[PDB]
Image (cartoon, grey):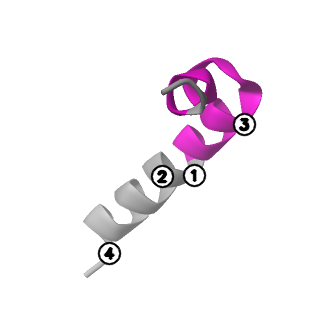
Amino acid sequence: GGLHVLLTATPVGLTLLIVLAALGFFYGKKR
């Protein structure tokens, strides 16, 4: 209990958020 939450604060977290969102959009439009 700590790092899991800190990840949201740290920059690394945000950097990953964009990636996850990117794949989602691409996958959604792709088929």
First in sequence: mark 4 or mark 3? Answer: 3
1 and 4 marks in contact (CB < 8 Å): no
First in sequence: mark 1 or mark 3? Answer: 3
Relative to 4, say whether 21 is above or below.
Answer: below
Q: Amino acid at mark 1?
A: Val
* Disc sitting over residue 19 in the figure: 1
For marks 1 and 3, give the CA distance.
11 Å
Q: Amino acid at mark 2?
A: Leu
2 and 1 marks in contact (CB < 8 Å): yes
Q: Which residue is mark 3?
A: 12
**Which residues are the magenta region?**
4-18
1 and 3 marks in contact (CB < 8 Å): no
* Foreground label between 2 and 4: 2
Number of marks: 4
Q: Which residue is mark 2?
A: 20
Q: Amino acid at mark 4?
A: Lys
* Disc sitting over residue 30 in the figure: 4
Q: Which of 16/6 is in front?
A: 6
Tell me the quarter of the picture where residue 9 sits.
top right
Q: Which of 5/25 is in front?
A: 5
Q: Amino acid at mark 3?
A: Val
Residue 1 on image: x %, y %: 48, 27
For marks 1 and 4, give the CA distance.
16 Å
